[PDB]
Each structure stands twice: as structure tokens, then as C-alpha cells.
Image (cartoon, coloured by chain):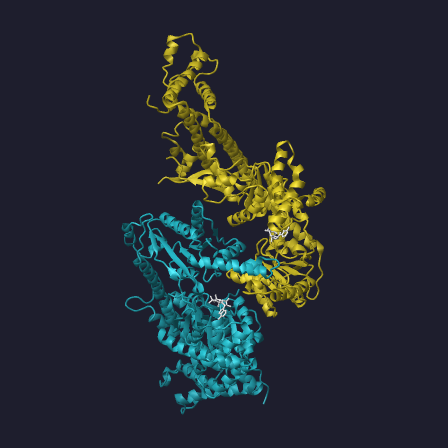
Chain colours: A cyan, B yellow
Amino acid sequence: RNDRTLRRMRKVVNIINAMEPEMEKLSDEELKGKTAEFRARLEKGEVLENLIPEAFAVVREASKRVFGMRHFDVQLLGGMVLNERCIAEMRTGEGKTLTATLPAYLNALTGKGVHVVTVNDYLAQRDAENNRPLFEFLGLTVGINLPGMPAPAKREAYAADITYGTNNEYGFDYLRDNMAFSPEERVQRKLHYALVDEVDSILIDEARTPLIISGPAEDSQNENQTLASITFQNYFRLYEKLAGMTGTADTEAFEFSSIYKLDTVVVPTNRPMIRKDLPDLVYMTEAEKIQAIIEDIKERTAKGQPVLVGTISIEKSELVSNELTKAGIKHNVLNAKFHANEAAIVAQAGYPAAVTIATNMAGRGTDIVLGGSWQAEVAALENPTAEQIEKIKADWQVRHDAVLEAGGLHIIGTERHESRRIDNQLRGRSGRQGDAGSSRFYLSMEDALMRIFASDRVSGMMRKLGMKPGEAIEHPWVTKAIANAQRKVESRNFDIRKQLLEYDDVANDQRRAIYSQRNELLDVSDVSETINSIREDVFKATIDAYIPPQSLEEMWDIPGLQERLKNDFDLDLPIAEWLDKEPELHEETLRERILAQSIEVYQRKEEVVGAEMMRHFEKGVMLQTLDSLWKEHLAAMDYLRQGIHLRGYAQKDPKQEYKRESFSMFAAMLESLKYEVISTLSKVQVRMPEE
Amino acid sequence: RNDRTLRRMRKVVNIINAMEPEMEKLSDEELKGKTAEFRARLEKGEVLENLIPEAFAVVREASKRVFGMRHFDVQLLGGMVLNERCIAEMRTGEGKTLTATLPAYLNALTGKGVHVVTVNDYLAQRDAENNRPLFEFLGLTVGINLPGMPAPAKREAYAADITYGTNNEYGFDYLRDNMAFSPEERVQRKLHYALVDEVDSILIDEARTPLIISGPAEDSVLIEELLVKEGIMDEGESLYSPANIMLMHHVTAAQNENQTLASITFQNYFRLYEKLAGMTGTADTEAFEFSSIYKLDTVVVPTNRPMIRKDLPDLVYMTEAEKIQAIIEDIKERTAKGQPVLVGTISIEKSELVSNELTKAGIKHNVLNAKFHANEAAIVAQAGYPAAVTIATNMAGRGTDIVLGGSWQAEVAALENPTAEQIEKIKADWQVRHDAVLEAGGLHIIGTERHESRRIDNQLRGRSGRQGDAGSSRFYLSMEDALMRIFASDRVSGMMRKLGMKPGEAIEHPWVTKAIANAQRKVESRNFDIRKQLLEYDDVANDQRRAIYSQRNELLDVSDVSETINSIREDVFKATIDAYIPPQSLEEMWDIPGLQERLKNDFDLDLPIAEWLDKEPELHEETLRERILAQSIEVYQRKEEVVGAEMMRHFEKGVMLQTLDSLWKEHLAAMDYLRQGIHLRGYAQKDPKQEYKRESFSMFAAMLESLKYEVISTLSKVQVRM
Ligand SMILES: Nc1ncnc2c1ncn2[C@@H]1O[C@H](COP(=O)(O)OP(=O)(O)NP(=O)(O)O)[C@@H](O)[C@H]1O
Ligand SMILES: Nc1ncnc2c1ncn2[C@@H]1O[C@H](COP(=O)(O)OP(=O)(O)NP(=O)(O)O)[C@@H](O)[C@H]1O
């Protein structure tokens, strides 16, 4: 499950490890050739996963030679996880970027492409350029997809062995491809593998975010409207293979599984994680909390230990700062108005006895180097030189080791966030890459968070334990109590969310159906058989409206049928004439004459234009009618859902009823798609010369 | 004007430079003793400005030895500007922070203190700590003032030769110094010299920002029936006199609550200093406002190396789409010659448009995305790299130097074990890039739109052409830009929509550039006119606060306040008796059923005085007044024999200060209510400004007389068990 699959993966790592000597002997150009060899074997029927050891050994030697970086064993494990339908949890500083080169290479081999998905355009370009030398070294091409990029350049990016771009541009390209009128206009290939770089934002926070293409199609002054829509969740769901990465930034494993059927695997850190996460401390009042924070700081800084303090607001950043100053403790506040000051502060935040106050600390942040960053120190130098550097490093080693000795970076959370993943991000700022460190969070009985115990009498019991000034005790049940509360908030929030996804699933299955139909049309030149086929459906249904099947003549509405055929099929037949003249004519033979006549008329239009022109007109009419009924259906499904509140209630589930109305409305649209296609083809004015 | 100042100052620079060998020959200890020598000369009557050449030369040699930096000739000039009541406009890259050591030193010599004013606490602390070794080398002490610092520590910081702190904290300390009950509680000295490190924000943007101390430190048709009745209001006295404003605010209204205890704006704080100066980059445009608000002259200091950035004619297009296309073509032409470009925009949405368009054109670039700060700093690093293109959205002022060719810093700043070979390689390869960027024209700046504030446009353009580097800038405009509403004519603007700009056919008109600059200047000036009216309202409050605090500080500074008390008690007793006995009046026209209970009620003074006058028909009105004063003195001296002189003198003083503070706080509240009650009372016609200044000064005058009365009433009625 975790260490069952991990102990199985460790066996493979040993084999990759056992292969390095073999790989070290290989020439650069022999490493290049392995890719072609792997593909030959796949062509002969080999199973991809059988290639992982050799493939991963190849990638690791290529990196060594190219980046001067050798994947660690835990990065091998990470890369195996990402080949499966999984989230690899890898802690910050663990080299997720380099790890991702592994499953990208592996899943590039079948020739079906890879989509590495980034949170923004800077990272897509940056990661494509950084990795392009590695992948070219192994005979693979690298694409980059950006907004604004012309279609032929996008096709090229999707045609590469491995592609980089944001979630957004991938999703938009998919939508635009399902508005194409010829398959050649498509930019994407089949959606094979999506490797998602930060799944918390991309897959969880953005799951239900619609991606929309809008337009003034406004067939009938004229408005904007949705022409094509998909949510992120339902986009990523289209891929054959989906995987992603995040930091020990978890608490949401159950959600990945619900939303995506993604398992999450906790990947072990390269070095033992030794940060001491100390029990949560609870105080009656904010003031006694702050005095406690100040006394911890005072104590640790006197020992040489740097501290980073996270708060939830500027106001609270100010308060602890003023109180530190009142206590004589030098520090810096990270002030979001002064970015240059911020980078300068951050740089020396791991310096002996440094104290930094940060307001709503981000995810990941700049690494805090213990003892200071000495690279900032030469960065400063205007003519850096040898003896000069060496003195700096050597003075730094001493500081670094003194900071480690003193316990590494201490993190203080002055409050907890309602989301523990945020708390976890702050805390993860310390103890990176094996470094000594610690963390402590402070709560008061005032703290907003003491409100997710949805009871003022419950919470205020903790008062009767006392919290008594200096005479703190520590109670670790509190830490788990608080963690559990945070768990229940997420879980409550997700139940709500999961109901909203069950509504989303109605639109998803409708979209999937209409698009797969649209794509079957798009993929062929000749839509004849379908046309012929729906023509009989349309005439049957149209005739049934005036001639109830197997009715006597007296129930028939021939006047009404005649006009209908005139009005909608430009088909003006003397049906009354027929009946009143042939006492042979039964209902079935009337149905045929009518059908036959439509056909004869259409065949002469074809004779004028030519077959090819006609085949492509049919196809375009189908796609175009499909598109405009879908647009109309999207708008109507939107009105339907937003009116979900007072429709299903007296023992019926709303939904059950929405699913009913939705089914009925989708069913009707497909009938109406056949109607409108045959109506258009029937009515197309062609100007006819003689014979 | 600027030409003559700089001429005379270039003369002094030549003297300074001639002194360098004298200073070079001095031991470090001899250099330090220059300070004491300057001060022995000042004690003997030397004029401070006679010292500038030697003192500057001393600071310049000190900086060489401590910092390994020798002030440039232009930094000497900036330093001389800053010793006068002037703004030294010194371009981004020019070493403002080092420049400021010079006037700080010199203005520290008289032993009266220097306040260096920074924008934030980081910079205060950093500057203080960076300059401490420099000023200690020269025999001076440096202080740092921060929020939360205990008063003893604040005292120490202000008692240092030079102090660093934010504007905010300086002003707050001033307010709290004026809430002190003894002079030894004060943390500041007399406000001598304020050197303001970036005056655009500190002096202009924030001129009118109130600093406020609040404190729980309170104590406790339709008009007609409201008006009628009760213990306060009942004569038939208007509920909406200025007088009765707190009352009316009460009916407006129908725990304990916090009020303003003290307030001052930055602009009025800084005007308290004996000397004021400050710095900013070539931004100007606001010289007229500095001069008008602060009486600061603005001297534009030349750059150390010639400033050769080529600031090209503004270009105007009919449509935004036409503008964007022109911006893309130029970026295309320049990047093909290897020249890097910085594109500044006014919106995220504008960035995304230009960016997507550059991608449609196959032009590699990076947007600076506000969400991704670590990306943004990596971007800025390579922004001066050949053919680099960077899009920034409402870029700030100054910002991080873009090094041409790239920073040969950031490259080794990512290299964890260099050598001679390596860096040497890095640096050599960087020189070729650098030299090629220079030769391609340096950094080209594109303003895709102009801001309403030309100062902002000038900041953006100033990122190019630093420290003598080649560079250029060009601003783009279209008829669809919000900036065409800075001209107040729809139709005047539309004659560009008659000289209608066409496809492969650019011209250029210098009058357009001039016309836009002039429109932005007419906008600045219109905004400042609006602001000046507001500063007039502020001047009413400043006048009253300056007067009240000057009174308060006189009291605080005197150990013994008896003579002030005795003097005001006669004042008070004379007027009070005037209210019932008209001067030189015959006994006939005297009211005592009003006078007797007045004295009893307001002063615990019960002198059955009709029965003097029944018993003695021989005293007369003046010897009557004499006796009435005499008695209160009697009762008073008696309370004091019980209490102690000392104890009494300090009680009287505290009572005067507490009364003044109560009356003052009440006045601040009533004025705040008048000022907003001065939005709709009866037309902006019958001048609302003017009437408010009158009622306000009227209430101020009233409060001054009421401060006398209340003190004497407090001192008359005070209980001591005999
Ligand atoms: N196997 C390795 N050998 C040498 N250096 C490495 C190795 N793996 C990673 N690095 C470096 O270690 C740092 C961590 O990179 P990164 O993947 O950005 O860390 P992360 O926190 O897990 N990921 P992210 O924040 O998404 O970029 C980078 O500076 C890498 O270049
Ligand atoms: N005379 C000098 N000799 C050598 N280096 C100097 C000298 N003057 C300044 N520098 C350096 O030039 C840089 C400029 O930064 P700084 O003085 O803060 O801002 P500026 O734009 O230069 N003016 P301002 O930003 O308001 O101070 C700093 O690295 C200084 O250390």
C-alpha cells in the first residue's frame, strides 16, 4: 500500500544501483542509443515497467554527465511512484524537479508524448530549457506550450517527446481542439500522460474551476456566451496516465483518491528528517501567548539559534515585533511592500541568533541557509577572489555548524491556520535536507482557531487547566485534539465539495458523450452513412407527428404534414393528391414515397456541386449544428443547476431530479441535432441548371 | 539658479579634493580628533558652513578607511545641498545612502542631534548599523529609534550624535513627549535637523497622513422640543452652535470608548525642525510642491558619469491594437540587434496582452508575475542579458539595478565551489556580453502607456542609463488610452483622429511629447490645488496645536508655576466679578444673588459679602475686589501649610497640564465633528472653509479662557483634611 509498494520499489533501486558500473563505461553516444534500443524492445512487445531499471540508470548517468547531478535513491523511488497513478509526496528541498526527469523519460518512450504541467509560464519555459540538454543527450525532443503561441508552433510542442506548459494552456488547447472543423487543425495528440508539478493547487484547489471559451457567436446588440467548457478535474481525468508531485504538504490524500483515483505515496527523504516538532502550547490570552513567544525567542537567540516567526496578519506581525523590541531583541520583519529588503533579510535569516517575523508565510519559500548564505556574501563582492572566497566559506562553516549545534532553525507559529497544510508549510521551512531544527505553535483561548471546536463552553474548559505564567506543563493530547479538529474541518468541507462534484459529473458525462460523437465525425471525410441513417430517423419522427403510426386515414393530418415538409425540408409534395388518387397507398408506402423524394431532390443538388463538396458540406453542417446546440444546452444546463434549490424536496432527492431533467434535456438535444442537420441539408438552396 | 549653486559648489569640491593629501597623512586617531577640533572652533564662534571643506574631507577619508569607498565629487555636491533647506535630486544608482553621511556628520557637530528619516525599520537598523563604524571612527555615537523600544533606550538614541528611525516613530515620540507630565519623561531633544531619505513618499505622498495617539482616556422644527429642557442647555441657546457640537453629536447618536489624545500630520511634524533636507531620484515634477509645502528648494545634482540615456519622442497611435503592434515590431527589431528590453505596463491585463502578442510573434520573454516573487528576482537578474525581454506591471520606484550583460554575481552566487579559472572565465564571458549590450544601445525601456503621474514614468525610464550606461526609452500612447482624459476635451483629443497615423509610415512630432508632458503637469498642478485647500484646513489645526503645546511645554519646563497661577487667578477673579459688578459702577448696579453663589459654587468661596457692605459703607468697589482675591489666597495658603510647598507646586503644575490636556482633547473631538459636519450644513456657497476656520479659532480662544477658569476652580475647590 505504501511500504508494500515501497519495499517492492527498493528492490528495483538496488538493481538500478547495481547497473551504474555498466552505465559509467558507456559512451555519450551509446547512452543516446539506449532510447532507440528501448523503443525497439517495446516494439517487439516488452512491458514498459520492465525497462524501469535500465531506463532510470540511463537517465541518472545522463544527468551526471549533463547536469553534474546524480539522482539519489529516493529520487529513483519518486520517479517510480510517478509512473503509476500516484501522487509522490516528496518533502521541500528534495529535488522534485530532477526527480520528474525520470518518469518523463520513461513515459516518453512509447512515442505518445508527455505533458509536464506547471503552475505558470516562467517555470514551463525554465524547466524546458533546463532539461532540453538532458533529453537531447538521450535522443528526445522537448516542447514548450505558451498562450498566444500560434497553432503550428503548438503542434510542434505537442509533437515533441516531452512537452511543458501550464494547466491552463493544456485545458484551453483541448477545448479549441473540440471546436476544430478539421482534424488537421487539432494541436494536441491523444492525452497520454500528465505529470503535474504541484498537485495541491492544480488538482485540488483548482479541481472545479471551469475553463471556458466564450464568444459572441450570438447567432441571434449581441452578448457573450460559453462555447466550450471543462473543469480541471475533468480535463485531467481524460488522460490515460495521471501523476503528480507535492511536499509533505498532505492532509488531503483521501481527496486525491475521490477526485482522481490517485493513490498518494510518501516518499522518504534522502537524509533522516530530524526536525523536532514540539507540542502545541495553549494560553488563556493573546498577551500571555505573546509573552511566551518572546521568552522562547529570548532563550533560543541567547544560545545562537536563529528563529523564524510566522503570523497570520500584518497587525500580528507588528505586535510581536514591538514586543520583541520592548524586550531588546533585534529582529527583522518581512514587509510585503519592500521586496528587496525581504530577499536581503531572508538571506541572513539562518545567521546565528537571527530573528525574522513573516506574515502569512507562502508555500516552499526561499530556503534558509543555516549560518547565513555565504553565496550572498560573494554575490556582494565586486571582485571576488580565491583566498577571499575560501575565507568566507571557512568563516561560514563555523557559523553553520554553530547554528546546527544550537538546534538549527526554530519555527514559531504564533497561530494555527484553519488548514493544517498551511501550518505544515511554515514548519517545513526548518529541518530541510537533514538539518537540525524545531517548531512550536502557540494558541490562545482567544485564537480564532479555537472556534472550529464549534463550542464556547467546550473550548473554555481549557481555562480550568490554568496556563499559569512561566509554569507551563505541555499537554500533547492538545496537539492531536487540534490536529483532529483541523481534520474534521477539511472533511466537512470536502463532503460539501464532493456533493458539488456529483452535480459536475452530470455535465462531465454529457460533455464526454458529445465530444466523442463530435470527434468521430471530425475523424472522417465522408459522413454519408450517418446522414442517410438520420434522414430516415428524422422523416419517421416527423411523419409520426401527423400520421400516428398504424392509425386510420381519418386521424392523419396531411395538411399539417404538407406544410411541415414545405416549411422545414423545402419539400412541397401533393400528398392529399396521392391519397385521394391511389386507393392502393397504405401508410407504409406513403412514408417511402416521401423519403425517396427527399433523396432524389438531394441527389440533384449533389449533381450540381459535386460529391466531394457535398460530403464536406455535410460534415461541416453536422459539426456546426452540434456546436450550436451544445452551446445552447450548456446555457440551459447552467440555468437548470442554479435553479436546483427548490425543485426536489418532498422525499425526492434534488438530483435524482436534476439527473432526470438533465438526461431528458440531453436526449432531446440529440434528437434535435438530427432534425436540424436534415432540415439544413434539405433546405440548402442550390441554383439548378436544366436537363 | 541651479547653475550658480552648482558653480559655487564645484569651487568647494575643488578645495575638498586639494585637502585629500592632508587627510591621507593623518593617523586614524588624528582623524577622529578632527571632530573635537571642529567643535572647539564652533565653541569659539566659528560658522558651521566654514567647516564644510575640512569636514567633508575628513568624512571622505574616514569612508575610504572604514568602507573602502571614497565619495565622488557629485556626492560632495549632494552633501553640500543637503546642508541647506533643499532636496538633493540624485539619480538612481548615485549612492544616496553614502552621500548622506556627509551632512549627517557636519550637522552633528554642534551637539544638537541629527534625525535621519528612513521609510521603514529595516533600513533604519541597517543604516544605523552600517554607519556606526564610520561615525565611531570619527568620534560620534549613532542611535536607532524603533517602535516598542522602551523610553530609556529611546532617550539614549536621541541623545546620540546621529539618530536613524522612521518618520512614523519620530512623530509618535513627539506626540508622546507632549503628553508627558515631567520634562525628564521626554525622549526627544529640540528638533534640530531632519534628513529625509526619500522625500517623494515621506514628504509628498504622506504629507497629510495623521499620526494619532488614541486612548480610552475619556472621563465619563425638530430642533424645538429637542432644544427645550435639561441641566445642560436650557437658556434658549442654539443646539448647533459650534459651542454645543459634542451635545448635538450626542443627539445625532440617539463600556467607555476611545478618543484621540494627540495628533499631528507628517507635513506639520517636519516643519517643526530647525533644518530640513532630503533626497530623491530625477523623478522631479514635484519641485513646486516641495517649495510650497516645506520651503525646500530642489537642486538637481549631476551624475558621476555622463547620463547618456536617449529618451525618444512619444509615439501616438489611433487604436490600442495599433500601439501594441508597434511595440512588438520595435521589440523585434531591437532584440534582433541583441539589445535587451524592459516593457512597463499599467495592468496585469495589459501585461498579458503584450505577452501573448510577443508569443504570437515568436518573441521569448518573461512577465514579472506578482504571485511568483522568486521567479521575478531570477528574471530581473537576466534582464540585461542580450535580447532579453521583460514585461513589468506598474513597476515601483528605484527597484533592483538591471546589470547589462547580466550580473556576473548571480552566476557565481549559484556556484558552490569556484576557482580562479572559473570566475575569471565567468567574468571574461560577461565582459563580452556586457560590452555587446552596450554596443547594442544598452537597456531599452518601453512604456506601453503613460501614467497620470509623470514621476512614475520617470522612474520607469530611470531603470535604463544607470551609471553612465547607454540606454533608451520610449513611451507609447493611443487615442483609446485613459490618459487622453487628462485633456478635458473629447473633441480636442480627436484631431489626432484627423492626422490619422498610417501603417508602414511613422513620422514623429516633438510638439506631441511636449503637449503630453504639459498635460500631465496641468493634472499635477490641479491635484495640488485641491490638496492645498486641504492643507489650509490642516493649518488651522497646526496653528492651535503649536500654540497649545508651546504653552504646555512652558509649564512642563518650569518647576514652579505659582506666579502663572497667581496671575491667572487675578485674571479670572477680575473678569468673574466684572460679570456682576460693572467697573467704576455705583453700588446700585451690582448683582450679588448671582455673585455670591458664583463664588461659592465655582470656587468653594463663601464670603457673606452683602454684610460687609451693610456693616462697612466705606470700603468701595476696588478695596472690595482686593479683599475677595485676598481670601482665596488665604484658604489656599492654608491648604499648602497642610500639604507642603513642594507638593503644592507640583499639584498645581499637574492640574494645569491635566486641565489643558482635557480641554484640548475635547477640542480635537469637537473639531473633527465640525470638519465632517462641514460636508452638508448649508451650501459650499457661503464659504464653508472660512466659516469652519472662524468657529474653530473661536472655540480655541474660548478654550484658552476656560483653561484659566477650570484650573483656578480646581485649585479653589481641592480638598485637603486640615
Ligand atoms: N540528485 C541531486 N544531485 C545534486 N543536486 C541536486 C539533486 N537533486 C536536486 N538537486 C538541487 O537541489 C535543489 C532542489 O530543487 P527543487 O526540485 O526545485 O527542490 P524542491 O523543493 O523539491 N522542488 P520545487 O520547489 O517545486 O522546485 C535544486 O537547487 C536542485 O538543482
Ligand atoms: N563613492 C562610492 N564608491 C564606491 N561605491 C559606492 C560609492 N557610492 C555608492 N556606492 C555603492 O553604490 C550603490 C547604490 O545604492 P543606494 O545609495 O542605497 O541608492 P542610490 O539609488 O544609489 N541612492 P538611494 O537609493 O535613495 O540611497 C551601493 O552599492 C553603494 O554601496
Q: Is residue B100 above or below residue A679?
A: above
Whether residue A569 is visible to the viewer of this picture, yes or no, is: no
The answer to which of B87 and A265 lies nearer the viewer is: A265
Q: Position of residue A247 (x, y in %)?
A: 43, 66
Q: Position of residue B679 (x, y in %)?
A: 49, 41
Whether residue A479 is visible to the viewer of this picture, yes or no, is: yes
Q: On the rendered structure, is B480 left or right of A433?
A: right
Q: Position of residue B57 (x, y in %)?
A: 66, 44
Q: Is residue A267 above or below residue A572?
A: above
Query: Image point 62% across, 34% down: which residue?
Result: B40
Q: Position of residue A325 (x, y in %)?
A: 45, 46
The answer to which of B621 and B379 lies nearer the viewer is: B379
Count of marks overlaid on the render: 0
Residue B101, by quadrant, is top right
Residue found farthest to the bottom? A584
Q: On the rendered structure, is B505 left or right of A603?
A: right
Query: Image point 71% across, 55% down: which residue?
Result: B510
The quarter in which the C terminus of chain A is drawn is bottom right
The quarter in which the N terminus of chain A is drawn is bottom left
Query: Image point 32% across, 23% down: which residue?
Result: B721
The answer to which of B665 and B658 lies nearer the viewer is: B658
Q: On the rendered structure, is B220 left or right of B358?
A: left
Residue B363, by quadrant, is bottom right
